[PDB]
């Protein structure tokens, strides 16, 4: 019907270690694409401080407290019967001196 | 005003797509003047032809590669490379066909 595509691409975030960090994207396609997030080649699962809030086309990755073990490249993968779309963003986590 | 060398922001390491489907991969970048974008697979440039399956759309800070009706022979290691008057950058993503 119509493959996935990004109305709004996910942007890099630079955050102080221990503070909140979020990636946001807006995904279109028909039927509405299912979105999952990947890091290190593996699909991320929800946890105590990682969740994946979504409101319609708007899909997000939320770290309630971002630690250095969370830094790196996150991939947003959107999927429906017509295709798949991929976009990445760097989360940078800054440790105080 | 000052030049900025091109810098590719996040590009995925590996992506997968089912045969016969559309694949899209978007990638942000910076650099001043606006960098020229080249997509290539196995060292060979991808040509965005309006009468074909490969299409490339470039803005000031974004490139999108769309492959329609993905064939098993479309798989391989794709390189995004950027160039302006102040330097270059490249990143590779491994595109897998299921």
Image (cartoon, helix red, strand yellow):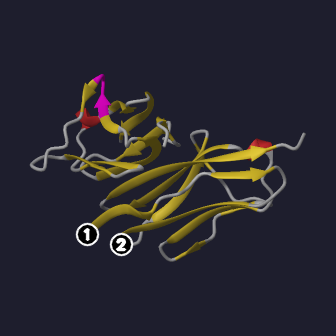
**Which residue extends farthest left?**
B51
SS category of the residue bearing label 1 = loop
Give the camera-side residue of A75 and B69. Answer: A75
SS category of the residue bearing label 2 = loop
Q: Is residue A15 visible?
A: yes
Q: Is residue A80 visible?
A: no
**What residue is at 47 percent from the left and 59 percent from the top?**
A9
Mark pair 1, 2: CA separation: 7 Å
**Residue on which the image places disc 2:** A31
**Which residue extends farthest front?**
B1
- Rendered location of residue B97, percent (x, y): 34, 39
Secondary structure that dominates the magenta span = strand
Q: Quadrant of residue B49?
A: top left
- Report the chain holding disc 1: A
Task: Report whether B79 appears left or right of A15.
Answer: left
**Residue on which the image places disc 1:** A1
Q: Does the CB distance between marks 1 and 2 fall below 8 Å?
A: yes
Q: Quadrant of the C terminus of chain B?
A: top left
Residues rendered magenta in the picture: B39-43
How crowded is the residue under tag 1: few (<14 C-alpha within 10 Å), some, or many (20+)? Answer: few
**Which residue extends farthest right?**
A97
* Rendered position, A64 above or below A87: below
Same chain check for tags 1 and 2? yes
């Amino acid at each position: 019907g119509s493959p996935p595509c990004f109305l709004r691409f996910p942007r890099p975030v630079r955050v102080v270690s221990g503070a909140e960090a979020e990636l946001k994207c807006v995904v279109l396609g028909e039927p509405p694409p299912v979105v999952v997030w990947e890091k290190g080649g593996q699909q991320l699962a929800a946890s105590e401080r990682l969740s994946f809030p979504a409101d319609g086309a708007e899909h997000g990755l939320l770290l309630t407290a971002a630690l250095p073990t969370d830094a790196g490249v996150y991939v947003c993968r959107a999927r429906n019967a017509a295709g798949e779309a991929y976009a990445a963003a760097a989360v940078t986590v800054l440790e105080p001196p | 005003s000052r030049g900025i060398p091109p810098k590719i922001e996040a590009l995925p390491s590996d992506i997968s797509i089912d045969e016969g489907k559309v694949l899209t991969v978007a990638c942000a970048f910076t650099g001043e003047p606006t960098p020229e974008v080249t997509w290539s697979c196995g060292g060979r440039k991808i040509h965005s032809q309006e009468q074909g399956r490969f299409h490339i759309e470039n803005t000031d800070d974004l490139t999108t590669l769309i492959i329609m009706d993905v064939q098993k022979q479309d798989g391989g290691l794709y390189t995004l490379s950027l160039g302006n008057e102040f330097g270059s950058d490249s990143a590779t993503v491994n595109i897998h066909i299921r």
